[PDB]
Amino acid sequence: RLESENVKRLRQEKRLSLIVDLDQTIIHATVDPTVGEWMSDPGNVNYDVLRDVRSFNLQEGPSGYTSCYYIKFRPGLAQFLQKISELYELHIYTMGTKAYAKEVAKIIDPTGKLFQDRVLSADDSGSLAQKSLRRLFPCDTSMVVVIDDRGDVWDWNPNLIKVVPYEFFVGIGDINSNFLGSNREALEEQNKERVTALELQKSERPLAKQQNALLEDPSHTLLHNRDHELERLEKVLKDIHAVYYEEENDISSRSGNHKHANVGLIIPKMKQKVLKGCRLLFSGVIPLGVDVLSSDIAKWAMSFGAEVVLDFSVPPTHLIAAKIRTEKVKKAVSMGNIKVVKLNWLTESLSQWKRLPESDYLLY
Ligand SMILES: [Mg+2]
């Protein structure tokens, strides 16, 4: 069959498989018409950083509602995809529509060389709330790595490399997130909701409002290129690849090629070094009434080796606090030997695969 033969082929090519999210992983998209105006004006403070933005029109829904999408490609993307395709067979897996995914692929991959037809979208993935490795590799996930800005859609799968969400168009989120986590609504209800959100973004012009506020106050320019995430990510993926093929060489030779390596084992071993020895207590971060140990932030932290505790019975190493005026903070301070830090210490450390100095994240 095809699946078992693809695994064999990849090993002969000495490659792995990479599932690549679009929105806020390798692109950021908006329908704010402000972008088109700024792009058309060489004199605009935002023009220079918009020069590489590309756009397309999509007609959407029963009524053929039409929007101009503006796409910012994350810095270094062309180079990143070229280099990483040497090591990984690339797939796209997005919660956007098939039409959207195809429009983006036409721009990043015009001749089909990088992704060919390996493009999964909301239309054909099987779910509007979660993604699954099994949609592509039902029987054997040992060679597949994921890059995605969201861990919740993957249930914090051990094959996931969560990336820093790309936010170039300041204040614009993920325009394709509208149906994450939820039940399946009637198609009529889905289209009403999307048209509504798009129309709202067009009419409110959040970019214009934010830019105007800054000017009314380089620091006055809204948009900037300050993202270097793909340079970091390249190194991680190159490491995973090299560790896999060294372990594969060892395991397969010792087993008469009956056993093999597994990135799902390799990746957690890499991650668990980062916050090894940390025991985290959260204060005012998880909402009252929400289960802490199954929360996204707890799962993210535990994937990087941190323990999470719920009280001081065994004193934590860190108190991750959102508000300063709590008995947890008072107790932590009065106890001593506990570092009290903003949430940012944790999210930025996890993001950089590197425990950052706590002294840089104190509360006051
Ligand atoms: Mg995304």
Image (cartoon, helix red, strand yellow):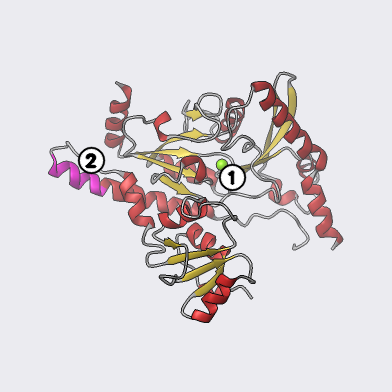
Q: Look at 46% across and 79% down and name the residue there.
A: 337
Q: In screen coordinates, is 17 left or right of 356?
A: left
Q: Amino acid at mark 1?
A: Gln
Whether disc 1's CB lies below 8 Å from ligand 1 is answered yes
Q: Position of residue 263 (x, y in %)?
A: 33, 45
Position above or below: 41 against 278 = above
Q: What label sits on residue 24 in the rendered view?
A: 1
Q: What label sits on residue 6 in the rendered view?
A: none
Q: Position of residue 155 (x, y in %)?
A: 46, 43
Viewer-side residue, 362 vs 29: 362
Q: Which region of the structure is painted magenta? A: 246-255
Position above or below: 14 against 207 = above
* Residue matched to label 2: 260
Within 10 angstroms of label 2, few (less than 14), some, or many (20 or more) residues? some
Q: Is residue 15 magenta?
A: no
Viewer-side residue, 28 vs 195: 195
- Asked which secondary structure carries label 1, the reply is loop
Residue at the top extreme? 62
Earlier in the chain: of badge 2 and badge 1, it is: 1
Q: Look at 61% across and 64% down and name the residue there.
A: 322
**Quadrant of the image for the C terminus?**
bottom right
Viewer-side residue, 50 vs 341: 341
Q: In screen coordinates, is 158 left or right of 99?
A: left
Within 10 angstroms of label 1, few (less than 14), some, or many (20 or more) residues? many
**Quadrant of the image for the N terminus?**
top left
> Would you identify the image quadrant in which residue 179 lies?
top right
Q: What secondary structure predominates along the stretch shown in magenta?
A: helix
Q: Amino acid at mark 2?
A: His
Q: Position of residue 265 (x, y in %)?
A: 31, 48
- Asked which secondary structure carries label 2, the reply is loop
Q: Is residue 361 visible?
A: no
Q: Look at 41% across and 44% down and name the residue there.
A: 157
